Amino acid sequence: MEIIRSNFKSNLHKVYQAIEEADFFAIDGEFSGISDGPSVGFDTPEERYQKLKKHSMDFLLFQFGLCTFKYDYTDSKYITKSFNFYVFPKPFNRSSPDVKFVCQSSSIDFLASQGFDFNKVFRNGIPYLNQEEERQLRHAKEQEELNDAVGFSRVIHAIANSGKLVIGHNMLLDVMHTVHQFYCPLPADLSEFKEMTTCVFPRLLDTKLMASTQPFKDIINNTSLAELEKRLKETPFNPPKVESAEGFPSYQLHEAGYDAYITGLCFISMANYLGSFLSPPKIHVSARSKLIEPFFNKLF
Amino acid sequence: MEIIRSNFKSNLHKVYQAIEEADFFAIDGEFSGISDGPSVPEERYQKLKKHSMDFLLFQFGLCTFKYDYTDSKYITKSFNFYVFPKPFNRSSPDVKFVCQSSSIDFLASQGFDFNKVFRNGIPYLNQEEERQLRQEELNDAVGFSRVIHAIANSGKLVIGHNMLLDVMHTVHQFYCPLPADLSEFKEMTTCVFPRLLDTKLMASTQPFKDIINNTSLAELEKRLKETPFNPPKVESAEGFPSYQLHEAGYDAYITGLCFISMANYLGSFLSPPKIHVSARSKLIEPFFNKLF
Image (cartoon, rainbow over all chains, first blue to last red; front, side, top):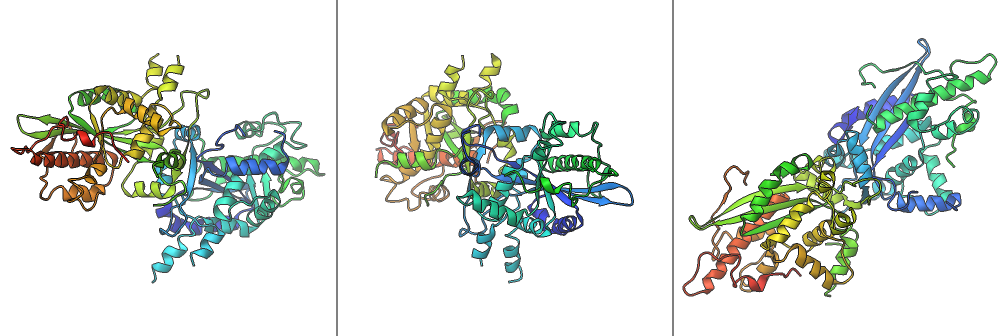
């Protein structure tokens, strides 16, 4: 589903429900760009975080893709619902903060070649407020515009509170943008950034990292999402039986929702392959299984 | 006319001719923002260069005015050019620009189509990139700068309203990046725009200062309809669109109409009085090349 501003309020209950029925979700986002200077080295994990927070966190995440996966046991298949949410920090009043973001020509050019509609962002973007901004901005329609101003952050709240596993692929920037924009502006120290992430994403998993770890490291040559999905269709892996839910669309031009979906199919093949190190070997391994626990909360 | 990348090369002869047959032009730009940090001393140049030049000028409105002596009326042609710095390759510079949320929101509420910029923008190259890059594929890279060069080589008067930022963005993006000294910025300005005139500055200078109370563009053109001013007789060119939502080409048009009412009012200080004053008259010389 393409979810914009005029659209957001009525589709929100479908999203909550998708989140609730799900075993896990995958996410992905498009940004207005990646780096303001260097191609981004002799840097500790904390110096890299500070270099990323300076040169990458001024760019905007303006398309959030969400794909929801639910296993049907009496059919042996996953059922998917995917969403594309277009977001823009439209200021509420002349009192609200006025965001300056950075746009990167090559990235805009890339998004355009994938058929991106910049009007869904710059005209129809869903507004949002972070934690402080919401509390700080505090008759029937007057209380409506107020609770509608938190906007897309409502969706981030539901994910965080679900507790359920959240999958991404090479998701550091995805996660930094998300917390920075919807929860709270990024702190100076990596230590406390790790504390915030835990409040927005208590269970994280990065398919690129998973694919870069044993026993996957010895089989997988390329961990790019495109090549990873291609590789996970052949032996010793098995493509999963997946189907979109009744009434929902289904799947190619790069785009958040699609990537979130492909990321999800990747995690599923990789997880199912772990079943083969059991006796007897399982063909199906849940997202809650203990085989998957050593891959959680990495992307250190 | 709405001119985008797919459409630029074929419409480029209508543009040249309109520039060549004109008496003067009016311009206006839309930017990705304006603020940076500050709000809402001679060296405003250094501030603006620090706080406003990272934003992008992505719609250039051009209005062409030709005087018809056999009718005593100006004839107009408006053009809206959407431009975007599409890199020539992953070896040439990758422009980062700043977008201002409130500015994007404002432009959205005026019906602005962002796909005209971020999908269909006309590319461009400044002085350095054009020379350093040394076939038709390359003369399409220069893109919109061809228009800027034609305006410059015409010698004719270029009008704007409160145009400092317009002219800075124009020089920056299409001629050469902004220099250190304001003096050398003026030298560059003289290459892009030999004759300049700012209707806001004109309206803030006697004898207009004693009469004009509000120099914002909408207020100015409204006051210039009533005495002692007289609205100028103006028409659109055979087969061209004509004139409402704030938008580069529209404001450029309104900017031209303001100049024309002010220029003519100056005609009233001659004996006998003239009801039409040319853009070349010495009556206007004292207002040229001033925009602070």
